[PDB]
Each structure stands twice: as C-alpha cells, then as structure tokens.
Length: 5
Length: 355
Image (cartoon, rainbow over all chains, first blue to last red; front, side, top):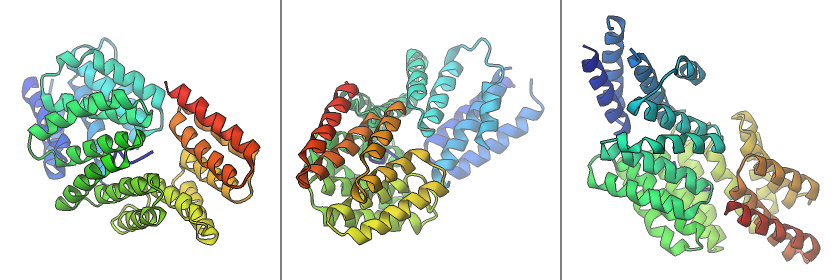
C-alpha cells in the first residue's frame, strides 16, 4: 500500500 | 466546574486536530491541574484525550498500553458523544496495530453515533480515517465516498493543511488503485508542494513515495527509484530512521531495483529492509521482504504461498494481490508459465475476495 500518512 | 474542564478538553481536541503541539501541551497541563481538585466519567474523557494526544505525538515523532488500560477500565454504561470518542479512538489504535477487522468494527460503531457530532471538522476526521482504512482494504468506492466528504470540510476551514495533504494522499492513491497514475500524480504533487510549505519532513517523504508508486505503475522504474531514494533520504535525515512506514519505501525500492535487472543492489536493498524490519519488530513488513527475497533470489514457491496465506489471515488481501502480481509476472517473463498460471490465479482470488 501507499502512504495515507 | 465540571463543564469548564470538559470545555477545555474540547479545546484540547481542537488543538490536537490542528497539529499544534505547544497548544496541546498547554491544555494538557491546564486540564491535569484541574483533575486533581475536581468532582464523573470526565476522567474517561480526560483519559480518552490523553490517548488521542499520544497518537498525535507518536505520529509527529516516533507505554500506550497503560492508557489503553485506563480506557478499557470501567467502560460501563457508555452514552452520548463520549461513546463516539471511545469507539473512534479505539479504532484508530487498532488501525495502527495492523488490526483491520477490529478497527473497522470500532469505526462502524462510531459511525452509528455520528449524528451526535456537531462539529464539521470532527466529522471530517471521522470521514478521513474511514476512507484511510477503506483504501488499505481496497474498498475503493467506499474510500472515495468518505474522502471527498472529509476533504471538502477540511478545505472549507483554515490551518488543516496536514489533514488536507493526507486527504490528497488518499484521493490520488484511489486513482492509482484504478490504474489511473496520471490522474494520481496531480494530487500527490499538490500535497508535496504543500508539504514543503509547512516543512513537514514526514509528509514530504510520503509524497515522494506515492509519486514513486506512480512511476512504478507506468514502468518508469528509474524515476520510481529516484522518488524512493529521495523519500528514504528525507525519512532517515529528519529523525524518522525507525518509523515503520519507511519500510514501505525500502520495500518498493527493492522491487524496483530488482525489476531493473540490478541484482546486486536489489540484494543489498532487500537485506537493508529485512534487517530494519526485524529491528522495528514489524512481522508484517518482514514477511513482505521475505516474499521478495524468496521470489527474486532462490525462487522458493512454498515460502511464497506460506507468506500469501499469512497475509490473508491478517485480512490484507491488497498486499496478497500485489505480491501474487509480482510473482505471476516474474515467472511469466522467465517462460515458467505453469507457476505463472498459479500466481495469476491467486491474483484473481484476491480480487474476488476484496469484493
């Protein structure tokens, strides 16, 4: 997954 | 003066959502001085805020279980918006512990009492955290439904730049999950520019990482490795050497260097990530570096399926699909179409499970 911070 | 302190807890929450640390510490000290000479479940509200405050601190600079003990102690006969804060904050914590089933259960219980929430900003917080866990679960349509509500409320207000940058992350990442990288680059770039405005190193590195995911989707592997290298630099040059999310960047660089047929650098990068993952005690990210090693080094397929099953029992079917995509493509390029068939079938299984 990507960074949804 | 129980209402006076509950009002100050409300202000404490407001400064927490604004990412204003000095104000949050001021109001934590003010409230704590009131708790000593005070007449309720206000002590839970105070504890709930001490919990939320801790989540903000951990996010800004990387125990908590003692605060969970005071939260989980004597939660008999909950009602009102205190029950909402309870389920919402416990869901945020469960999300931070890779507990997706529990975090979704708590988020849905917080959703039932959402009409009790009057502040549009607080509802924007709920909508953003729900869209976040829905993107991680690749419920793309549901995540988009919540993220547009949240970002509209945030953008209507001022000084919520941090939360708006995270909303840009979620929006672009859902476009990327729909095979629209050129639609995701504008949002990630916009968030990057605003990330260097407030000089938020963590957000800058995360913007570099998401943009590198865009170059990875377009098979511009060099530009992806450039984003991944600079994101690793930004993370490990600004006090984020031991933040778990840096593994997501190292891991992508490990795929990218491996896809560029640079076997030696990929060997070193997979080693860097496996070691740091064991150091930060993250079994999830560790087994995901184990997949890339067992696939791109010694072609250990039983290990690949063991990891894929492990990742499924954690309800992380998204990462299951990504890894089976890596293996099916790699074995297809090596003319090993039998095992490439098997892993393409697992991509199909994961996609159906996500529905």
